[PDB]
Image (cartoon, rainbow, N blue to C red; front, side, top):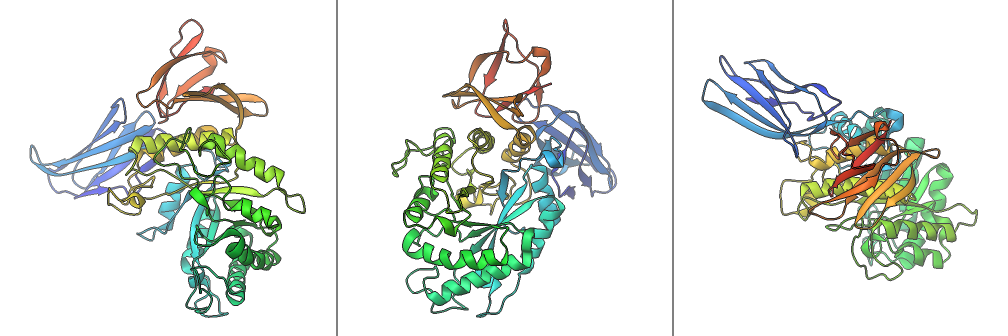
Length: 490
C-alpha cells in the first residue's frame, strides 16, 4: 500500500513528508513533485516501512506522482496534488476573506480547520437548522456539530457566521400554510425564540447570524419583513452585540441589484436589521465583467458595478439611529463543471482583489471549501477548493497566495483598467504591492513604467513562485494571464 499524508497542504519551503511506504522487502516508493506551468520537479525515495520526504525549494501547486515498485515491476501507483503555500502571520490574515463550510465527511474538524487556516481565511459560514434546535415546541437544544464548528474556529482564530433557518414543521405543523417559511404569528414567535436561544448559548462566540438561506419563495415585504420584525427585537435583547443579517441572498440573481433590500427599505423596514446578505453568483463569467442582468438599476452584474452600487444604497438609506446597514457577501463562487480548474483559481483571486479595490463588505464568503461529491457534471459537487479526498485544487493555492499578499492593505490606485488591470494596494498612504492580470483568455504582454525602483521590487505569480523582472528601458515587461501576478515592494 501507499499511505498518503491526510494533510496535502504545507506552509513554506522545505522538507515535505508527503507519504509512507507500507510495502515489504525490496519495494521502493519513488515520489515526484511537479509544479504547475513550468514543471519544476523534486524527487525522493523511501524503502519498505520508511517515510517519503522531498526537499521543496520553491512555493507552488504541485502534482504528486507516486510509484511503488520491486525492481522493474510497478506494484502500485498514485497521483494527487500537493499545495506548498506561503506562510501567513495570524494577525496579517484578511479579515474580509470567508469560506462556506459543510460538515466534514470523516468528522475530523481539526484537520478541516487546519486546511481552512492555511488557505488564509478568517471567517467561516455554516448552517443551523431550526428543526435541529427546537425538536419539540418550546424545548431547545444545541446540536453537537455547532459546538464542534465553533470550538474548531476558535483554535484557528476564525469568526464563525451562522445561517439559521429551514422550516420546523415537526414543532409547528400549522406554521407553514402557503410556503416553507413561517407566516403565522405562532411560528414567527417560535422562530424568533429558537434563534434567541442559540444566540444566548453562543454569546459573543458567534457575532454574525444570518436569518434564512435563500428565501426566494418568501416575499421581502409580505412574508420576510413580518418574520424579521419579531426576530430582530427578540434576538437583540438577548445579545445586543451581534450583527443580525437579513436577506439570505434572496431576490433576483441573489440580490446584487437590491431585489431584497429595496422593497424592505421602501416599506420602512430599515431598522429591523443590522445588515443584509447577497449571493451574487456570476459563474461561469469573469468577476470583472460578469453578465447582463434583468434588474435595471445597474449596467451589468459584476464586482466593479455591484460593489459601489450597494455601498451607495447603504450610505443613502441609513437606519433611524443613523447606523449604516452592512452588506455581507455570504456566498460567491465558481465551479469546475462550467469552468476550468485554473479559471476557478483565477476568479477566486480576482474576486478578493476586486472586492478590496471597491471595499464595502466586511465578509466575502467563498462557496465552498470542499467538493460536495465526485460527479464531474454536477455543478454542486465542484465548487470546492479541496476535492472529496481532501486533495487541493488550484483554487486552494490561489486563495492562500492572494490572502498572503492582500493582508489588510487598503486600495491605493488604478494604474490600468479595462481589458488589462494594474492595481496598487497599501498601508497608511504607502503602496506595498501591485497586482496585474488580463481578462483575455490567451494572455497579453504589457509594459508598465516602473512605479518604484527596480531593486525594491519582487515579482510573484498566482502560485507564490518568484520570477525575475524584465526591464525594457525603464518599463517592466509583464506577461499577463487570467491568473493575477503581484509586484511586492521591498
